[PDB]
Amino acid sequence: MPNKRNVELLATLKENLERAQGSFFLVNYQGLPAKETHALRQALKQNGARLFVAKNTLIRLALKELGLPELDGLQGPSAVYEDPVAAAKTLVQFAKSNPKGIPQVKSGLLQGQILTAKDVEALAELPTMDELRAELVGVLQAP
Amino acid sequence: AVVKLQLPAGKATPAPPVGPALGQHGANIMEFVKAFNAATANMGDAIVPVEITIYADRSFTFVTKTPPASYLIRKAAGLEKGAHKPGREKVGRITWEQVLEIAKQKMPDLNTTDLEAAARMIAGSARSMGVEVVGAPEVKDA
Amino acid sequence: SRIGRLPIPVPKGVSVEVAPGRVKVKGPKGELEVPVSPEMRVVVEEGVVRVERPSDERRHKSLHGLTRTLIANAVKGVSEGYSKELLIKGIGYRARLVGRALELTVGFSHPVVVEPPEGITFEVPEPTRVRVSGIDKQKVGQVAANIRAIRKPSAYHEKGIYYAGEPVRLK
RNA sequence: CAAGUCUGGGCUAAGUGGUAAAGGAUGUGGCGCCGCGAAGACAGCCAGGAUGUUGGCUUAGAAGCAGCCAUCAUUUAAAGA
Ligand SMILES: [Mg+2]
Ligand SMILES: [Mg+2]
Ligand SMILES: [Mg+2]
Ligand SMILES: [Mg+2]
Ligand SMILES: [Mg+2]
Ligand SMILES: [Mg+2]
């Protein structure tokens, strides 16, 4: 039982759980047809905005560590993510949607503090609730 | 996929292997022996890559993003007309002055941009050619 | 690890009888007896049929996998048991059907007339290719063997009767 | 061919027995050690294995696969010019 240094500095480096607060965290695999998405091997000199390895290593037992509340997007645990630039700019910089560029990227599970589901359709399709919040300055009660 | 070249220094040569073999390749070759001929014109021979693409039909694609790995080598760097028995003799020795930022041209695409990257990439067929050249006198850890 | 001997096979439109040293399959495409060892209980269960062995020693284990694969194979037997391509590469070479019988020409002073044994059926759609309809598995793989053996498939030249792959070609 | 198809335990599938060695062997049975494994090993199979590239040296060209050789260096789940 080495528990090889492949798990040791790649078991999170306890990072992104405490880095770019370790929640909102969500969907979408360790890899499928390698042509398209991208800033794959291009996030300026690192892959600080992607991940490297190991579904069995960390996710099975890593632990509860470092949070924000519950859950649930679409589904549950098999393969996940890493970034600081979540739901709004999570999708003007990566992972467009439905199906995608390449052939239709697939699946994962989330947990932030905004109460609800899917994480694909309404939250993650270049939704400019930044440029449609100068719409609220007179809405819902005013004369 | 769809890849080959056109070269060497200037006055492009569509020879029996370098451009008359454009049949079931792209075939609009009267005006595009001239729209590449300013994209390898007035640069100088050391390698000068050629990027060529695929289509549904017949013409009009891109050229190149960088000529590295022996080019910014044998202009003035490393004095590397790196003679036969590729050289454990110092066929020519430098530092990272005509290697590191002679080409920040490298930065378009080798997937790592910050310069211990495609700098030391092109010090592959330059630096480790027998005389692994030097980047410093070895930083002095402390 | 992960032995071919003790998984559990399959249902749905096929029979099973267990004599003490033979199992009779008898599904929709015909029937297949399976000569089988008289050690090795072959116990039949719901829509599956496992085989277990009386000891766990080197000589009983080899007999275990064999008798599983032997039954399973007779069950895909009685549902689509045929196979075997025989693409006929090379220039003068053409196969054709006459009667129930295959007559192929691979460059001798004569055509070679194969006839099909029972439970075997010849197909030559597109006559540089000839498929073998079979129920069994091993009689099928045989008649395809024999057909292939008639002509080469060299080894210096892409002529002969070919299964699949293999550009071998020495020069 | 006189007296056990005697009694318990295990071995061998060669008619060895009923023989001849160096040497060999996933025959087979038994005692050991050591390596890797349910933070998931060994088979398979599913996916990806590059760029600048043609590495330089030789060169109608070798662009891993005609070669004599510096065989780099980043990058990166991971990929030997
Ligand atoms: Mg007597
Ligand atoms: Mg006795
Ligand atoms: Mg004897
Ligand atoms: Mg003898
Ligand atoms: Mg011996
Ligand atoms: Mg043994």
Image (cartoon, helix red, strand yellow):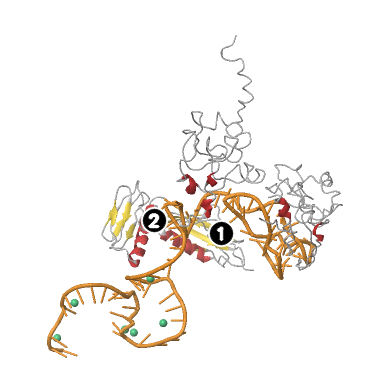
- On the question of residue C115 being in view, the answer is no
Task: State whether discs 1 and 2 lie on one chain.
Answer: yes
Residue C23, quarter of picture: bottom left
Q: Amino acid at mark 1?
A: Gly
In the depicted view, which residue is nearer to us: A39 or C93? Answer: A39
Determine the secondary structure under disc 1: loop
In the depicted view, which residue is nearer to us: B63 or A58? Answer: A58
Q: Amino acid at mark 2?
A: Asn
- Number of marks: 2
Label 2, residues with CA under 10 Å away: few <14, some 14-19, many ≥20: some
Q: Chain of mark 1?
A: C
Which mark identifies residue A129? none
Residue C64 image offset from top left, x and y in percent: 34, 61
In the depicted view, which residue is nearer to us: C42 or A71? Answer: A71
Residue at image position (54%, 32%) is: A120
In the depicted view, which residue is nearer to us: B62 or A60? Answer: A60
Residue C124 image offset from top left, x and y in percent: 51, 54
- The quadrant of the picture showing ligand 1 is bottom left
Which mark identifies residue C73? 2
Residue at image position (54%, 47%) is: A13
Residue at image position (54%, 45%) is: A30
Q: Earlier in the sequence, mark 1 or mark 2?
A: 2
Left-right relation of A106 to B97: left
Give the answer, above or below, for where A91 lies relative to D8.
above
Left-right relation of D67 to A33: right
Residue A31 image offset from top left, x and y in percent: 56, 45
Label 1, residues with CA under 10 Å away: few <14, some 14-19, many ≥20: few
Q: Which residue is mark 1?
A: C165
